[PDB]
Each structure stands twice: as structure tokens, then as C-alpha cells.
């Protein structure tokens, strides 16, 4: 139907906007600490601690399959990256500290993303 096509164009345009959001958030992680899944070869107990791992490569795979229906879903995955890290790692670690800085800097980006999503519809 034509309605289904219009819905699909809306999803495509959200995907475009979320790709720009993802790029801007990933720039806030210049150490690439959050770029890839935590390796279960290198951290064998990880899934005992963290039940829903997340990372920017995993998000990018979902994004490119148009698997984010709205901005809430995307933000959920970004918050997982941060929150997982802040539980597994202690406060005095480069990993924790990177996550705090990513949260703080990413907030700015996400605030305007939400306005753009609502504004453009």
C-alpha cells in the first residue's frame, strides 16, 4: 500500500537521523572503549554480571537493519552501554570514567535529537 511505503520512508528518515546521532555519540568515546562487544574470551565471567551487553558496533548493526522504530529504543541501547560499564567497573577505573564522560557529553546530543524527532515527526 501507499501507507506502508510512507511508513517505510519515515523509518528510513529516522534511521538517517539516528545514524548522525550515533556518529556524534561515538565521537565522544575517542578511546574506543565502547566500540565493540566486551570479549567473552577475555572476560569469561561477563554474562554472570551483565545480562544485556551492548556496544556501538552492535547498535550500528541494528540501526542498519532499520531496527530502531523510535528514538526511545535507540536511547535504551545507549544507556545500556553506559550503565553496564558503570556496574562492572569500579569508580576508579578508566572504563567507568569514560562512561561518565560519554553520558555527560551524549546528553547534549540526545536532547536536540529528541526535539528533531518530534519537530520533523
Image (cartoon, rainbow, N blue to C red):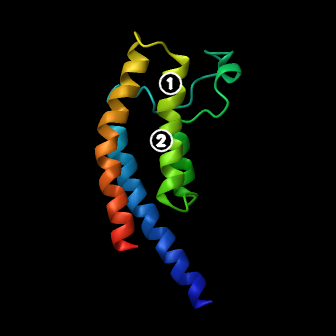
**Which residue does the image show at 38% across and 67% down from the upper left?**
118
Cα separation, mark 2 vs mark 1, equals 11 Å
Q: Nearer the viewer, residue 94 or 40?
A: 94
| Residue 87, percent from left and from top | 54, 21
Residue extending farthest top: 92
Q: Secondary structure at mark 1?
A: helix
Task: Say if 52 sits above or below 13 in the image.
Answer: above
Q: Secondary structure at mark 2?
A: helix
Which quadrant: the C terminus?
bottom left
| Residue 71, percent from left and from top | 47, 57
| Residue 8, percent from left and from top | 54, 75
| Residue where numbered disc 2 is placed | 78
Q: Earlier in the sequence, mark 2 or mark 1?
A: 2
| Residue where numbered disc 1 is placed | 85
Visible residue check, residue 93: yes
Q: How many neighbours does mark 2 have within 10 angstroms: few (below 14), some (14-19), or many (20 or more)?
A: many
Task: Say if 31 sits above or below 26 in the image.
Answer: above
Mark linked to residue 5: none
In the picture, residue 65 is in which quadrant? Answer: bottom right
Q: Nearer the viewer, residue 32 or 49?
A: 49
Amino acid at each position: 500500500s501507499m501507507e506502508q511505503v510512507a511508513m517505510e520512508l519515515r523509518l528510513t528518515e529516522l534511521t538517517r537521523l539516528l545514524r548522525s546521532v550515533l556518529d556524534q555519540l561515538q565521537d565522544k568515546d575517542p578511546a574506543r572503549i565502547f566500540a565493540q562487544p566486551v570479549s567473552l574470551k577475555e572476560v569469561p565471567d561477563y554474562l554472570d554480571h551483565i545480562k544485556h551487553p551492548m556496544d556501538f558496533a552492535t547498535m550500528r548493526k541494528r540501526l542498519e537493519a532499520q531496527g530502531y522504530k523510535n528514538l526511545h529504543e535507540f536511547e535504551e541501547d545507549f544507556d545500556l552501554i553506559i550503565d553496564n560499564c558503570m556496574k562492572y567497573n569500579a569508580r576508579d577505573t578508566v572504563f567507568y570514567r569514560a562512561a561518565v564522560r560519554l553520558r555527560d557529553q551524549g546528553g547534549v546530543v540526545l536532547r536536540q535529537a529528541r526535539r528533531e524527532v518530534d519537530s520533523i515527526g
